[PDB]
Amino acid sequence: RYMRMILMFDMPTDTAEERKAYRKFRKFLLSEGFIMHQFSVYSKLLLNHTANTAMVGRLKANNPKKGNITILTVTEKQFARMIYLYGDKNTSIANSEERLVFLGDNYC
Amino acid sequence: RYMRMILMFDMPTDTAEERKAYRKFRKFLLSEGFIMHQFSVYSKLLLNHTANTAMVGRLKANNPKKGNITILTVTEKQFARMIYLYGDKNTSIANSEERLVFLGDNYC
Amino acid sequence: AGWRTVVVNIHSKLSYKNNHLIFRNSYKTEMIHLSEIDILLLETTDIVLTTMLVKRLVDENILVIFCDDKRLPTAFLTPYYARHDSSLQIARQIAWKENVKCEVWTAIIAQKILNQSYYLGECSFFEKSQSIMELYHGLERFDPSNREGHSARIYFNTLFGNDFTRESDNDINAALDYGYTLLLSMFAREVVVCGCMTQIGLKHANQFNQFNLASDIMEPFRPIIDRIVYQNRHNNFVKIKKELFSIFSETYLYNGKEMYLSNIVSDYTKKVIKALNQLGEEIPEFRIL
Amino acid sequence: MAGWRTVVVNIHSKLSYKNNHLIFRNSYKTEMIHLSEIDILLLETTDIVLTTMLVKRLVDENILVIFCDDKRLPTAFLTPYYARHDSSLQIARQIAWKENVKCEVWTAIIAQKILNQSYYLGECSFFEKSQSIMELYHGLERFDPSNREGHSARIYFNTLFGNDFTRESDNDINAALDYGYTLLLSMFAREVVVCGCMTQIGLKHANQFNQFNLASDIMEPFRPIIDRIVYQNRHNNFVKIKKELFSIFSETYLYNGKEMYLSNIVSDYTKKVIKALNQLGEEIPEFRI
Amino acid sequence: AGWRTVVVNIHSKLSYKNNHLIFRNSYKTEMIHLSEIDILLLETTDIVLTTMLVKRLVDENILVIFCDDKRLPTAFLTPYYARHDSSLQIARQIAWKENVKCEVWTAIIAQKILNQSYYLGECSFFEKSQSIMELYHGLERFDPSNREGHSARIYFNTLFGNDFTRESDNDINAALDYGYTLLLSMFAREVVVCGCMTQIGLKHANQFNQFNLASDIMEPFRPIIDRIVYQNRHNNFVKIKKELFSIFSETYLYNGKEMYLSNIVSDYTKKVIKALNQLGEEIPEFRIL
Amino acid sequence: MAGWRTVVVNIHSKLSYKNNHLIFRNSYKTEMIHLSEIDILLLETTDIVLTTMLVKRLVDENILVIFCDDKRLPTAFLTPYYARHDSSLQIARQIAWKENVKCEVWTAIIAQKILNQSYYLGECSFFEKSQSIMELYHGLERFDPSNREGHSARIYFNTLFGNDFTRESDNDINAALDYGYTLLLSMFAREVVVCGCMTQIGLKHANQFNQFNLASDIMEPFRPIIDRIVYQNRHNNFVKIKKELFSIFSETYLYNGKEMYLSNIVSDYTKKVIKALNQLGEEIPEFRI
DNA sequence: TACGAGGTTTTAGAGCTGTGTTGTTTCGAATGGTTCCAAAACCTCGTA
DNA sequence: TACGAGGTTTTGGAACCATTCGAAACAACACAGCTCTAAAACCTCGTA
DNA sequence: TTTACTACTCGTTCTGGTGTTTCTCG
DNA sequence: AAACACCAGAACGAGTAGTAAATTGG
Ligand SMILES: [Mg+2]
Ligand SMILES: [Mg+2]
């Protein structure tokens, strides 16, 4: 089944090297397909546990080694049970897991 | 089994009313027993699903109605699978789920 | 009113902030939510408390057990006002009929003797278990023949040797003394929470040690401590106390449920009190099986 | 054992133990009290820091310590497991109070209250209403079956604050009256638990949800003290009346033919009322404004 | 090389940024990770593309299918270099033996005829299924008797009526034409990814429509489209196309596995190519059962 | 259908369709080309923005569009489902190239390369090494079994860059040589795919991991162009040599007795080499520096 | 008469709690594999 | 004799992937309840 | 000894803006 | 047309510090 993967990070910004690490890590996270759930919180949709293992391996390879960075993997059913006290859910297809995606008329 | 409950919020700070709402919400979150997992991210340990239902009811009662606030409930086993790329896990008893807690000598 | 049992052993200062027990040692600062704490046990005589924390602890019905210099319990806080309709419960307790009290005490002493017999049975000591079971039948209302004493005597002599006695000063006897004043604290707290009083009890015609009702209800639950003390008879006092602290983390089968000792104590106390004051309930059953 | 002094801690302080001395280390001044002269330690405020060493020593010296909450009301007390204070025996006496002696003491207390209301009404130059209340005082009977107290109270309130005045209203006079009555109730409950008796078993009041029935029964004659202060500053906001109400702590009143502070009056009054109820003596205190 | 099939119908601009397909309509901006996209299908003739996005799409082996004014596919991108060892695969393809090619084509045409027979069997049209099964046995190497044509003729006449023919211009025939050029695109992409060429195929002695190998491998998979077109014979073209788009979201049983059509197509193509070029594999089996 | 002009888009531009005209809307200047005069549209840079309307019309007019990647190498091409460009037939011819004609054309090409190396070495006044390379040229045979090309390219490099030189090294001269060779390889691959023939089937090169075997085989004679520029700026960092290497695009060379830009020379050379390989004619191009 | 001082029970939800249970998720371990590339391994032989 | 120009296979590992499966986990639902506060009755009987 | 309020003050986070560069076997 | 570097420059998120107040039936 489809996995979801939430990465939460707090990184120092005191030194220019730390800001380099933060910028490069954000670039990597966006390039690998992480949607901003909130500020400093990112989510990625994975097809299966093999993708999750590959992605955690890639993250360990590209670990900035600064700040506090944690990962939690939850099933898509578990992620769908998330309660929204306020704000609006992100309705982009990147969050959704539909195989057949229509940009425009859905013929329905 | 023991539940764990992660609350993530982004709140506006433009107006004094928004800052008041943020301050009151943080006070409420800390008073109800939320440990700061990271900045803007809090976690609460719940004994069971009854406690989870009661706590989400309390949060809905004390909803600041500002910003984007979301809740995810995961099992303690699921929370234990969290991967720490960097930083140190919080080792306080508040994070732990041990019934018998020793402050000092554990007689072992 | 929670699950965590908190034991403090080091010199520190205990304070209050935002429903939290602020524990600030010179090395570490450590915060515990008051809703989680169930029993607070201060063995070390160097802990510095504050009155606001005491008020907030008794507000949440948290057991606070102070200890002497030798780390043995010496006193514990019980709240004056633990139930909203405390006056009604006290008035109903004052009007307890002697017949109902005698019947319920007979039921609970039968539960105690039966639990002792079952423990001797599972202990592979078959013979003495039958003698205790026989003594159970001879027991009547108010136990005129003191069959409860005879069962306790054979129980102790079979578990700890014939030479052992309750009044001896041997180490495992101090272990039972420590254990029984840990159950008695919880039972006193629960009977106070039920709005009742510990002074007026079922037996002895109100001749009170201030814990008469709690000590009366505790009777079926003493085999819990007796088992832990028995199977660790070889170890020293500190190890036996460490194992005794496992009653707060172990689940016991009560009313077809696997509940922790706190919930079993609360349920048993509430059901006994409801069977007494209103006569509109059935006597509970706790089985060590 | 336990001596004679009752030590009340009502201000911010740190209490510590030293060589059989309790160290009242208040901010303003530091005092030392020998542990043999202390019988009851009443920690009424929540600004106090205490040590476990003090708790252990106070238990060993058989002293009763009583913790009160933010509202300066007794909320808990330390009960040693083995050695008990004398005040515990008082509970037994409270359980056995004859109906007739309770009748007589309650009737005397409410007679004092009615006479005090009449005296104050006469003091405010309402001589006709004072005479009416005095006649209702002549109408008194055992346990007041004819409800002379209620009619006297309505005459009193309608005379002081106008006929439109009602207790259920949400004006500032009612709030001030409630606050002052709460002050007196806290005082009387603290002095009742000091005597060892419970506040949940009253002479006349039997409200389930009330946990200070006996405190209310004793404080009835002292209500005109609050009423006079409220009436004297009727044309003011609640904060001004509260600032004037705080003067009852630092004022003096005539009791037993002496000018005594109101806290001492309350303590001595409570002790004498409990003495009269215990059937040790039949003297009933008399407080008149 | 992903799962999402992306269909674009509205006038917009398609761009590239950080491995994402930046879709920026005047109303919405919407980003899709390139790893997720498997097929990109641009029906509307108003989409504005960029060359860098085209390069990145062909880098990830994403099928890009352009469409005419009538929303029917007209062309699709195939990469020159899709496999690292493409030269070796092309050289091995050039040296394909005619015997192995004939045997594999016989196997796949038998698979096609057998799938047609099974579909007619499950369609409750028992009689024609037996005739197709009989025609299957008569088929030999290179199909001299054109039994494949006879099976297709009876299949179409049984499903869509005897009057129906493949060359007719009726609506459901345009539906099959749309379906078969959606399967052919994926098969051509997969045979290019395998390093091979679509021009040189098993049959017709390299007489190429530029999709000879893909059209040859497609044969067992045409019943997938034929079933969807058949069961929606009543609906109009748009509805049939909408239902045809469900091949990208439906799981089919292949090799004892419930795999999506993309994975089945990929694995089947790889196994057929491995059975041809190296003669070191077994012919795959796709069953519509 | 498709005309004669090949339109190469190498700069940032937006291409749009209008009334049977392709609108080359470059930043510097806007041009319009009738769609009947265009035979191949080669989008080599990644700065181009194109529309689906253009793609549809170019498919209908039977035009072949070839997309290249960041390295200006052909990466994809648009294949219509039904109507095909003439260049597709070229693939068939590439599949059937006789061994002897490939032998002859490769031998002529490598003879040109060796002669060019000798000519340049003589130009740098190394007459003895030039004579040695000329003798190795006389040692040539069919498909160069004696490896005269290898020893010629060893004498060439050791003469130009010293005896310590080695292509496996990581100095700046080697990096510049690699970059210029990449430039020429990209040019020749783009001109090979324009002719419709593949780069993965070469005359002599058969490397599996090489996907530009034909491109390398044809570009062999042009390597001295890069070698001369690298040697002329040997004592410089890589960025300066790259800036000088970009002059090959805007320089002129003598081919077919005319001063032609190097891109036109490459295109015409590739077309004539493919013509010679197709056995249509036996004329082999001759490029000499 | 009505209100309402002095009070006492009744209800009526509101918020809170812990454990069983039955079917249905879920988790890795397993099972087949798939490209991709950089480092070897080989050829010829001419000039150092 | 060696190196390496022109080259070609060969071979590990690295990174990636999709479906299964068997036992263990988990999620609301369902239970037995619990405490607590306010909002209603009810009383007596003076003084408007 | 707490809470409740008010600033202030640093860290943390992301977006917009401004250049500079964009073919490294065969 | 896109990546990569650098900065600003507003939005979030907590921690600290100074001040005022702390019994609202019976
Ligand atoms: Mg964060
Ligand atoms: Mg946040």
Image: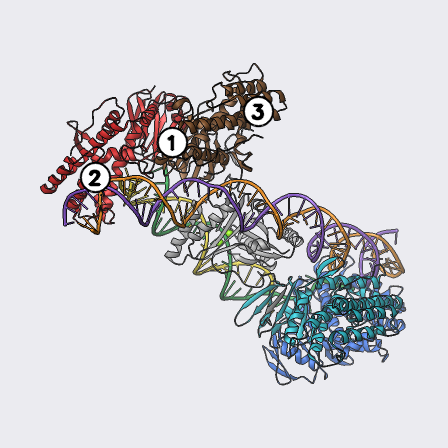
Chain colours: C brown, D red, E cyan, F blue, G orange, H purple, I green, J yellow
* Above/below status of I4 relative to C41: below
**Kind of residue at badge 1:** Gln
Give the percent coordinates (x, y) of residue C109: 49, 25
Give the percent coordinates (x, y) of residue E20: 60, 64
Disc 2: which residue: D147
Q: Quadrant of residue E211?
A: bottom right
Residue contact at pointers 2 and 3, CB within 8 angstroms: no
Mark 2 CB in 8 Å range of ligand 2? no
Disc 1: which residue: C93
Disc 3: which residue: C117
Q: Nearer the viewer, residue D9 or E264?
A: E264
Q: Are marks 1 and 3 on the same chain?
A: yes
**Kind of residue at badge 3:** Ser
How far apart are labels 1 and 3 at the CA level? Answer: 32 Å
Q: Which mark is residue F161?
A: none
How far apart are labels 2 and 3 at the CA level? Answer: 61 Å
Q: Chain of mark 1?
A: C
Residue C44 visible in the current orientation = no
**Kind of residue at badge 2:** Asn
* Above/below status of D9 relative to F86: above
Q: Chain of mark 3?
A: C
How far apart are labels 2 and 1 at the CA level? Answer: 29 Å
